Image: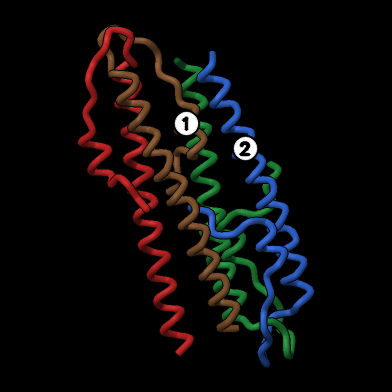
Chain colours: A brown, B red, C blue, D green
């Protein structure tokens, strides 16, 4: 299926306030790393598609 | 350079503070993040297979 | 990256030839319409994602 | 209505014969992936429009 979130969306996500909700620093630092993972995967899919496209064109 | 698996997203726990984030909103957000990790993993898997097959065919 | 091609890739796509081939004008002009569908789909996803964002603000 | 073709239209498209025309395997297999993109876009749009109905209901 398609990807729900961009790395932009991950970063822009705001959460409402809740008394005794999750520690904001823990969630924020966690999503900081999740952002890096979205960027890596998005770039990895692009390079793989580019490799396929080059190989198909080679095959031609 | 991948830091997390979907397993790690699911297993991630957080402390609480008085001015915290709404826990349902976070958990419901991370449930979709898990879906995205697994979609990416499966998409990468299938692409690396298409690449291996094309390389076989180029020989 | 669940979408394989951009509209640019459709535009750039080249084919070799064979003896019992497909008519080049027919394929070409068909892909010129596929190109429009890719552009339309990309702009519709972009407009819908904007409606979703705005809705989160309200 | 602004989409010209359905994924099923892409599949059903026939091209006439041209001697030394385009390689059928290359065109067919290209269009197989175009099909997957029409299916993906159509699923995606539906899914975005559902989320919109969801946020309005909420």
- Residue A11's tag is 1
In terms of depth relative to the viewer, which is nearer, D50 or A35?
Answer: A35
Task: Write the residue at 29% across / 18% down.
Answer: A23
In terms of depth relative to the viewer, which is nearer, B21 or A2?
Answer: B21
In terms of depth relative to the viewer, which is nearer, A12 or B55?
Answer: A12
Determine which quarter of the picture holds residue C21: bottom right
Whole-percent x, y for residue D10 in the image: 61, 62
Outermost residue, bottom direction? C19
- Relative to D32, residue A5 above or below: above
Element type where label 1 sits in the image? helix
Whole-percent x, y for residue A21 in the image: 28, 14
Mark 2 is surrounded, within 10 Å at the Cα level, by few (under 14), some (14 to 19) or many (20 or more) other residues, namely few
Decide if residue C39 is on the left or right side of residue A12. Answer: right
Determine which quarter of the picture holds residue C5: bottom right
Task: Write the residue at 49% across / 45% down.
Answer: D43
How many tags in the picture? Answer: 2
Q: CA distance from mark 1 to mark 2?
A: 18 Å
Decide if residue D1 is on the left or right side of residue B39. Answer: right
Q: Nearer the viewer, mark 1 or mark 2?
A: 1
Task: Write the residue at 32% across / 46% down.
Answer: B3
Element type where label 2 sits in the image? helix
Quadrant holding the C terminus of chain C: top right
Whole-percent x, y for residue A46 in the image: 52, 58
Mark 1 is surrounded, within 10 Å at the Cα level, by few (under 14), some (14 to 19) or many (20 or more) other residues, namely some
Say which residue label 2 marks.
Answer: C46
- Residue D54's tag is none
- Relative to B33, residue A17 above or below: above
- Relative to A8, residue C15 above or below: below
């Amino acid at each position: 299926g398609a990807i729900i979130f961009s790395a932009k969306d991950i970063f822009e996500q705001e959460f409402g306030r809740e008394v005794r909700g999750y520690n904001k620093v823990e969630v924020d630092e966690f999503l900081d790393d999740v952002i890096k993972d979205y960027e890596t995967y998005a770039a990895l899919v692009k390079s793989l598609r580019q490799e396929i496209a080059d190989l198909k064109e080679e095959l031609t």
